[PDB]
Image (tube, rainbow, N blue to C red):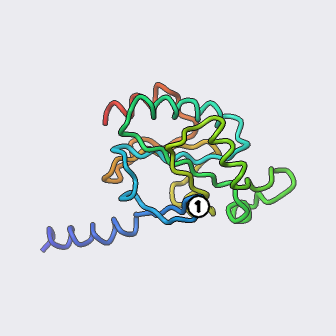
Amino acid sequence: NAPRAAGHSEEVLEREASFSLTTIDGEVISLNNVGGDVVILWFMAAWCPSCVYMADLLDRLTEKYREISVIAIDFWTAEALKALGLNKPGYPPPDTPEMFRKFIANYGDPSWIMVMDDGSLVEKFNVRSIDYIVIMDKSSNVLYAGTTPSLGELESVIKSV
């Protein structure tokens, strides 16, 4: 029975492919806990030069499209840096939760979920930079993943869905 086996295989694969997030306050969540139709995972760091402009874009898209939920994922943590070999004087020290909060208060939006990553999500989503965007729908289809997408690119993606 190929259709039956295909369906069960999907069950196993979907669960393996799934992820969870730890919020800045220490709460474990998944996609079910997120409100929008469109989920944007934004992998960033409080010192990232380009991230100020990215925050500007996400603010406007948040205001324009109520169905978007932004999850700000600061992966510039001691655990992630150690895993990646970036725990060296040539790189900034880990972001404190205070620095992360201050960045989001200054440039981002109060409705956003804030998450700090230990390198797990960096590995999961094949994150290529400190200003990296993954856009997904609620079925976990990936609509875009890439470093520093333009406003035009983001708009095009949101409009298609």
In the visual, does 53 lie left or right of 4?
right
In the visual, does 22 lie left or right of 48?
left
Which percent across, then down, holds residue 13? 34, 68
- Identify residue for label 1: 25
Up-down relation of residue 11 to residue 69 (above or below): below
From the viewer's side, name the closer residue of 83 and 102. 102
In which quarter of the view is residue 83 placed? bottom right
State the residue at coordinates (40%, 40%).
68
Up-down relation of residue 64 to residue 44 (above or below): above
State the residue at coordinates (32%, 72%).
12
Instruction: Please name the amino acid that badge 1 sits on.
Output: Asp
Residue occupying the far top of the picture? 152
State the residue at coordinates (37%, 36%).
66
From the viewer's side, name the closer residue of 35 and 123. 35
Which percent across, then down, holds residue 100? 67, 49
Give the quadrant of the N terminus: bottom left
In the visual, does 161 lie left or right of 101?
left
Residue occupying the far left of the picture? 1
Up-down relation of residue 87 to residue 5 (above or below): above
Up-down relation of residue 121 to residue 129 (above or below): below
Which percent across, then down, holds residue 20? 47, 64
Disc 1 crowd rating (10 Å Cα; few below 14, some 14-19, many 20+) is few
Which percent across, then down, holds residue 152? 46, 25
